[PDB]
Length: 162
Ligand SMILES: [Cl-]
Ligand SMILES: [Cl-]
Ligand SMILES: [Kr]
Ligand SMILES: [Kr]
Ligand SMILES: [Kr]
Image (cartoon, rainbow, N blue to C red; front, side, top):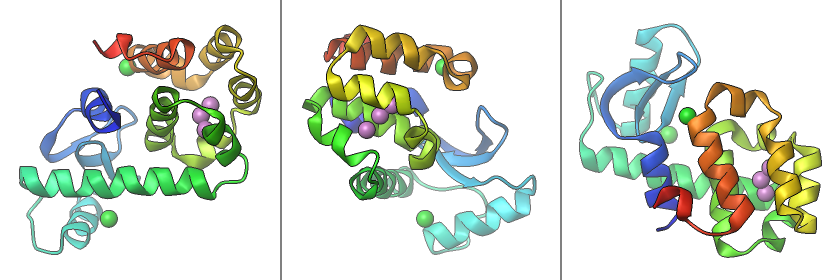
């Protein structure tokens, strides 16, 4: 297991524009296109991201290309964020994949808002952090995915994905 395989399980792969769990236009492996309710706007952003007139449809390869860019951006976002970097650097490799997952889902900002949990993770208080992490809109809205990520921080193993 690794970060790619992990997010590929949590996000799925769809070659035509679809709405995600929040009703926003997305494509591929969880690539958010726009929060706008306009399909045309979505189609606009997709073409711009791909570099061709796609007509709302992309290939497997193109999806994978966006995904790689998205994972890279997520990592870079963490490393550049002053509240996140220290936590991430204190973690082992598995737990770091959990942190990248959360960032890919909710954005750096979002994650940077879990103050209390960030601190517990940094102190290595796993059980305590897992309980605090569950007290969130994130967990109530996508509970099965949240449970998988939380178990990953809790145990430091890939069992929830096995
Ligand atoms: Cl892009
Ligand atoms: Cl879920
Ligand atoms: Kr983090
Ligand atoms: Kr995190
Ligand atoms: Kr977090």
